[PDB]
Image (cartoon, coloured by chain):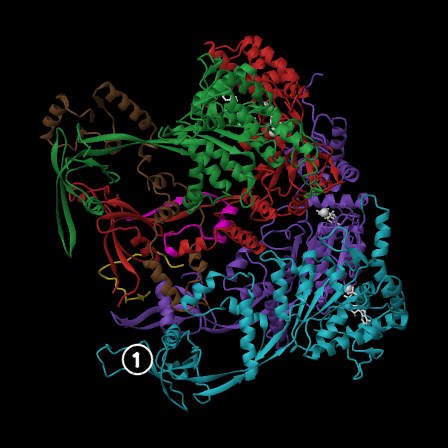
Chain colours: A green, B purple, C brown, D yellow, E red, F cyan
Amino acid sequence: LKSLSLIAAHSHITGLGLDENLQPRPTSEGMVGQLQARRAAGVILKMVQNGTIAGRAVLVAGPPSTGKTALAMGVSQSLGKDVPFTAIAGSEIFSLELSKTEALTQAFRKSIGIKIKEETELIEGEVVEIQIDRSITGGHKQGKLTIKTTDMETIYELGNKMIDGLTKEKVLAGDVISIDKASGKITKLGRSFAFVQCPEGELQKRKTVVHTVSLHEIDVINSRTQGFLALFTGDTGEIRSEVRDQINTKVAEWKEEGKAEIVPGVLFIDEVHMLDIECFSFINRALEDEFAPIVMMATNRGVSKTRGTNYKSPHGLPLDLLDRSIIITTKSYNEQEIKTILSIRAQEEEVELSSDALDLLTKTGVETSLRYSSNLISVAQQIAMKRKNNTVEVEDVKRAYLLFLDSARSVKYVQENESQYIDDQGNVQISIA
Amino acid sequence: KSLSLIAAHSHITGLGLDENLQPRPTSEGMVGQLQARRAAGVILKMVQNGTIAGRAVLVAGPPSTGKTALAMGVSQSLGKDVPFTAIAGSEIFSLELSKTEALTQAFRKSIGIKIKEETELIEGEVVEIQIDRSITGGHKQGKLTIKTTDMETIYELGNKMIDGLTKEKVLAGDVISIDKASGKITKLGRSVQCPEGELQKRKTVVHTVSLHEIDVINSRTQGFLALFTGDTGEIRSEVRDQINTKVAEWKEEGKAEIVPGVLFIDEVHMLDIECFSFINRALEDEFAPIVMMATNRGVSKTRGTNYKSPHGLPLDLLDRSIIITTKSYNEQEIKTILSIRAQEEEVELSSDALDLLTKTGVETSLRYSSNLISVAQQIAMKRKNNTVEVEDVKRAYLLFLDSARSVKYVQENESQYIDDQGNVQISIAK
Amino acid sequence: RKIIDTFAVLTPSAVSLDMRKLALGLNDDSSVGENTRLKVMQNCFEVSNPLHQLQTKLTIAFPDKSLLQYDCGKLQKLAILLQQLKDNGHRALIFTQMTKVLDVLEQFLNYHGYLYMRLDGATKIEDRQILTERFNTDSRITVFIL
Amino acid sequence: MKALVEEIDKKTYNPDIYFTSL
Amino acid sequence: VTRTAAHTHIKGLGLDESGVAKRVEGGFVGQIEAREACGVIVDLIKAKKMSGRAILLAGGPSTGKTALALAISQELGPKVPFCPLVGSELYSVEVKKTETLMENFRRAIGLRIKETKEVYEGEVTELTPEDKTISHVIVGLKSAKGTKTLRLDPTIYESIQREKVSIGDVIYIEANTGAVKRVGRSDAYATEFDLETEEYVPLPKGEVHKKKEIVQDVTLHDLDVANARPQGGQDVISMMGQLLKPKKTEITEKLRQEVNKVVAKYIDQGVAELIPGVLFIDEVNMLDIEIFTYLNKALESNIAPVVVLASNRGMTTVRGTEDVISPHGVPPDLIDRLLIVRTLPYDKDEIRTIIERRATVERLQVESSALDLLATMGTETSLRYALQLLAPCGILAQTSNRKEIVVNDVNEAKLLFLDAKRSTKILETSANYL
Amino acid sequence: VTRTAAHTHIKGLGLDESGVAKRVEGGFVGQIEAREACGVIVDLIKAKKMSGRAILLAGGPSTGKTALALAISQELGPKVPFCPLVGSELYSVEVKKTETLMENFRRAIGLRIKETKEVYEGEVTELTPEDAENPLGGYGKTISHVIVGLKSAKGTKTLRLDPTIYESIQREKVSIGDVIYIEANTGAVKRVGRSDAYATEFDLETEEYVPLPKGEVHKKKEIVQDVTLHDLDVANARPQGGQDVISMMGQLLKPKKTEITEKLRQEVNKVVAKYIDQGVAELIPGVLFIDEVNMLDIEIFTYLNKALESNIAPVVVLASNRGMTTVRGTEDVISPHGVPPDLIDRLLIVRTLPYDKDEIRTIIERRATVERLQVESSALDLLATMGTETSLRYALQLLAPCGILAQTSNRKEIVVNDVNEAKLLFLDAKRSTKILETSANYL
Ligand SMILES: Nc1ncnc2c1ncn2[C@@H]1O[C@H](COP(=O)(O)OP(=O)(O)O)[C@@H](O)[C@H]1O
Ligand SMILES: Nc1ncnc2c1ncn2[C@@H]1O[C@H](COP(=O)(O)OP(=O)(O)O)[C@@H](O)[C@H]1O
Ligand SMILES: Nc1ncnc2c1ncn2[C@@H]1O[C@H](COP(=O)(O)OP(=O)(O)O)[C@@H](O)[C@H]1O
Ligand SMILES: Nc1ncnc2c1ncn2[C@@H]1O[C@H](COP(=O)(O)OP(=O)(O)O)[C@@H](O)[C@H]1O
Ligand SMILES: [Mg+2]
Ligand SMILES: [Mg+2]
Ligand SMILES: [Mg+2]
Ligand SMILES: [Mg+2]
């Protein structure tokens, strides 16, 4: 809530949309079709919410336009809060100043999270009067405060830290403040009549405090003194394995202690069809690690030459990954399913579509691609408002189609437009004669 | 009291030559290679000759033939106080240090310099300590009687010495050593130590050092910790020129004298052509140590070039260097070396088992038997017998497969493992 | 501050004393000026830092007060059983044989933050009636120690 | 070397005094 | 509750006192020669006299190589320093690779030490320069029965005054390290302020001075990095030195010489002791020929402890080479110094046994017929595929509100999951690289 | 005692006053053309009028390119600056090679500077500031300017001293009665130690008790020290150091090397021109010598194409030993000695020559004299022969083993048996490759 979410291709989807028996509905919670894909996503969701097992990774593949990252975003938002989810681009790991392997280790460690619980006490009430006893030279200030609520009205002496805090900020006796004795923080809630705060109930309460923390930040702050600034800036790396396994043992004994509970998150890695065999071997090893969070791995390339090896590795991946990784495959969408997805998008972005206009938009999306339809349904809004009506007509979308080209038709055009452009050598005819 | 364990070279302690450069067939653990040991004596006479410099010698041969053992034996024959440096060809390849200045530093560290300095030491047992002073004005006048076997002398101590004596807690019966120039104090025992002789003992302190340390010190005020941690790099050559001139004048006036060191480089076949040229040009240096090459690789393509130079090295390097090789070992050499392993690592192998191990070493390799004799110890003591029999040797042979046996095993099991393309069959059916 | 003091546990098990002084080169014998070291020591004395919290957490592993009951397995179940007992709304009678476990029990109970009061040989003669009546009567006290 | 923490008294001890006998 | 990933089913190698590998022990099946060779390594490292030998595991996928590494690590015990490693991570971007190799070799060597620290605690009654004064401060610690005054170094007093201690503050101060830390204020001053953020704690019990022996273990690498660069400090110059260089640097040969000399002196003193370690490096075929030719010398070292390797390839070209094709991608020069332990694959019965054992540790119950199924399709595809599908089958049984995995469960699991073979097959019929 | 490393046998070209090179002179036998050309190059550099010229020396190995370079360096003299350089030395890691080669170019030329300073000595008795009896209404009379009567036995003067020189006095922690040494301009303070008068005060003292050096208080000395240009370059770019804390921090800031901008160089050039107009300094040219140039990157060749265009470029002599070789850093750019033609357009080619049997005999006997080792005629003939058919270098390398074999036989002369045994125990490249042809496993 209260967070920015602009119009995006993954904003419309909200949750997986599948029953308690994990049979998805044909159109529910943002997705249309891909029933087997959605039920597999629910399978992964129950895997991650169980949390008993670790070291699980999956392959989602197929041609483009199959909603792979759509399903990834759906399962991520189904995870929602109370669980960390990390999405990392495959090409992002390539760094020249940061070691690839330990950066990958900290990428895994970011997914793993630790929740620590503690109970703190606090006093809340309406301030009554402000009185202090200090000296101009000798200091030794002795402040006193009268606090009140709906039932209790009492006076307390104000210690040196509290009087310093009360002086450091402009305070009014009509203000309502909350103080935690252990930490000494001052929480100025509101003000009395000059003015929103109206305290009630017990004067002093005790409440629990929970910190959602990932193992990665423990590791970086405990690696060295400058770990704090490295975390807040990103200029870290090459963390020694000694602190690594020491913190691993510490969190293991804390988990068996019951003081704090671990939450093994989900890691998302993308377009790994372009990557290194170093990465493949290291993740092959790391999947067997005891502290291995569930890893989501996505790809789009079929058989191709894996970078770092001469041979064309099948599926763009080495066989060792395929030995330990389970595959999830997604099919295409029918014309009716594409129309339903377009209707869902239109409802999300609130543009009126004519029935014939929407039908021809669907047929031309099936003809060319659905990304083309996604951008056409956006430009149709401005085409329709330039004629001063939110409804999008057939002429709006046809004007958009004749205005913007598709990839295939532009390819054919440059086939008839070869001479006007340089070749791979660089030969062009800028002239006309 | 050096910390030493069993190793592939810990058995040999010295080459074992004669006055006329005649190698005893079994000397100081070094056996065989009569010509190689005579060349070792020749390079010995080179290094303790000291009057020659800029000499490069090449030692080559088949793998596992003990050329590294020859170098280790040579180093043992040199003994202490002679600066010897042993390194491979991979340490130089670094990113914080480029190859050229790394090789320059490798040359520089080789040669050492002897520095002879006289020191004044005062060592004797104390009788009592009495420091005069002011309660708030200072005015410290420390006095303490120093005794030994033949004097009982009171000494008035200056401000620095009594400030130190306040820094380190000492008592009357404690004995301390005093040096006039430094003013430092060293106490070791209590009436534990029995001092004797004169208090004003005038003994010298002699310090040896390579010119690398003084170069690093003069390069930078942080050079102390830089050499203590190795994070140096790219020292200006004008510093090298001035330090070379300074040590030259030191040599003429004789306060300090140089000790030409010995450099050992291994796996030169993987060295770069730029490094080869740097060696070729730096050999002409007057401060060029005696360096031997250890190339275990024969005809191969020199790194950085597409040309398959002989011995893996360009002929330009070979022209200004001499080459000697090493030969194989007849079965009696294997017998002798495995006997030395048995005595060194304390193996009471059976005579028939000794012959079987000799055969297995001869047909397969020397190091295979060198490890089999080690594993036979536990293969025997698991049944609680100190001696090792033939069945233990056969058990070790069958348990730990050989390189050729593994090669054959994978030749009919190519599909069991991945290929150059990487494909592998995991299913056991169809 | 809270997170940096709750997640700083390790220590550099090995360190070389007086190497910090030679890291900058300041010591009794050095090539730098005689009072250069004095001046840098003095200004470092006046120069302030906010990182000293991490410095004292890393240099020495302070035995935080939390581990009083994390080192006691009995206390691990004791905390949860008192939690469920107060959730049900019941008082308890607890008995031991040695007063040292009573002592550690009172420190633990003050740590968890309860109003309570103990009875043993150290108690005077007069307070026995008041403790008996306060526990017998309906009061906020729920744990009574013997 | 010198111990960082050393025994210090108030009656017999004084910063200026340093006497050690048999 | 319990967490596992393809391991933790190993509680040991599972041998006897005579060295014979039991057919089923410690959750192990088969590999009797491999288990006996692992026991040979066990009583090699228990002798702790051998140094500089290399033993690698030759096996394909699912051959139990890293499983055997887990077994040897488990039987080694916490005292024995075991350092698992990956042949791909040795490539370093800030320091040379051979430096990292020597660093991990030095990490492998561990050594127990015994030491005694001096502990001082109490409440400080005076913080005054001695008197005509210098940057020294007398501090008087008051314990329950301890009453002493201490004069301290300028640096430790600087750390004290940066701790914001005062009179009435109980502190914990050490004499050897000199680290400063205030416990809090005495309970006698709790009544002085009705409210205070600062917490009041009782006066320390006992006498101010304390002694205790410490038997903490330390690897030689930790000592080398301790004397190579400073580690901690509460005075400003300590942070000055730390921030002067945070970059990790190599270690000079003479530094190794002096550290081994000093530890030799300490072990000669009769307190220090030495224990070798075991280095396990995953897929040693992944690293380059440079590391191979450096290890050609590194193996011949003296203090270099026992190292165990593994590979998953055969007659393959060596990295960094063109015509140098070698078994396991390892050049012949190193394999002459290498010893190999042969591994064997698994057939139907042992595959079924390992699956049911890890299901027992998985806390999942499988019916006999479903066991027959998982034995069946766990062979024509892989054992690892059935190993992965074990958990989804149990969860599908759970969704059906049944506690027994049935043949139907594995049926839908294999229907809605496809293996590598099926992925390749459906890739064969591709319109646009499906 | 006497150390020789393939050199010290040559004492320069040693040409005649007419420039003709005699047959045998200064470790050189024959080789008239190259020696005469080198003497012509010496005449070029001694002209002190021309700059930017360069020359490359060409030919097969073992012909004495290093010998000729060392000869010209020796005859130029230590006063004339010289900067040796190897091709592999250029490739650095901190800064790009252009900065390094400009650094060497500046290092080539030098400049001697005339300077005069003032000398002071004597023992210390007074540590008092200016009394300043007049308050003037602005001074609570006191100053950080300690007036010291410089008590030398021959003179005494009271000096108003700067706070820096008095701070350095405090650094020495001087007391009453100890010799001091101060400078008028820099104010450098060094003490030989406490006087011998206070020696009897302390039975022991770390401070050394020294007598007062003889001489007047105020003494004036002049120096004409020669300092190369790039030492001043680095000093101007980075201050060298100082005893003060501010200088300590300043030199702690940036001690690593980086590029050098031309503006400071031009300002230094202008102030040096002002000095030479004043006559304070006089410039001297420089020589830069580069080793094994065939490996240089094409970028280095392109930059050196314009480096000589600069007016500050001194004479740079070059050596190469290649034929039809492709330029390193290129693919199809092949040329003699592996150098692009654009560079060699402005260069001058000089070629060395091989030698006849008598020349090998002469160089062998000259070497034998260099290592004071006496040889027989038959052994001399065998060495000369095998040097002709194998190489000069192999014979030079095995010269010492022959003497060692003679010595271990208690013989002071090398015999036929000595060289035969040396050939038994050592093999050249030819039989090395002959043996390695018939190799079981690359023997
Ligand atoms: N079932 C679905 N519900 C909603 N949107 C979908 C669905 N399937 C596909 N999409 C759309 O298709 C796009 C898929 O893009 P992405 O998953 O990043 O890669 P690819 O185009 O290869 O599948 C998403 O932006 C999503 O909006
Ligand atoms: N003459 C010998 N005396 C003793 N040991 C020998 C001898 N020859 C070979 N060895 C042993 O054989 C091993 C060969 O190892 P190494 O020298 O590294 O291989 P290479 O000879 O290929 O360099 C050495 O460790 C050495 O212990
Ligand atoms: N003897 C055995 N008993 C039980 N499980 C085994 C045995 N041997 C191998 N495994 C299993 O086979 C899997 C493969 O082992 P591992 O060495 O990790 O991979 P690889 O054999 O491919 O190197 C492991 O997860 C392990 O649980
Ligand atoms: N004409 C010559 N007269 C005397 N010595 C010579 C002559 N030519 C070569 N040399 C010898 O060659 C050695 C140097 O060889 P060098 O010039 O480095 O070989 P390259 O020709 O490959 O540069 C010197 O020690 C020198 O004695
Ligand atoms: Mg996608
Ligand atoms: Mg070898
Ligand atoms: Mg494995
Ligand atoms: Mg030459």
Q: Nearer the viewer, residue E249 or F64?
A: F64
* Ligand 4 within 8 angstroms of badge 1 C-beta: no
Give the residue pinned by disc 1. F129
- Front residue of E141/A148: it is A148
Residue at the image point whose x is 85% and y is 78% from the top:
F23
Position of B8 with respect to A177 (left or right) is: right
Horizontal side, residue E15 vs residue C77: left or right: right
x and y percent of residue F28 in the render? 81, 75
Residue B82 visible in the shown view: no
Within the magenta stretch, is there residue E43?
Answer: no
The answer to whether residue F161 is left or right of residue B25 is left
Q: Amino acid at mark 1?
A: Pro
Task: Identify the residue at the far bottom of this view.
Answer: F154
Does residue E197 lie above or below B322 as drawn? above
Of the four image quadrants, the one with ligand 8 is bottom right
Horizontal relation, residue A37 to residue F292: left or right: left
The magenta segment: E208-236
Q: Quadrant of the N terminus of chain F?
A: bottom right
Residue F424 is situated, as x and y percent measured from the top left of the image, at: 85, 58
Q: Residue furthest front?
A: A433
In the rendered view, would you say B334 is above or below F85?
Answer: above
Query: Is residue E232 highlighted in magenta?
Result: yes
* Residue closest to the eye, A141 or F400: A141
Q: Is residue C57 visible?
A: yes
Q: Image quarter for residue B20?
A: bottom right
Numbered disc total:
1
Residue E386 percent coordinates (x, y): 59, 18
* Helix, strand or loop at mark 1: loop
- Residue count near mark 1 (Cα–Cα under 10 Å), binned few <14, some 14–19, many ≥20: some
| Residue positioned 21% across, 78% down in the render | F137
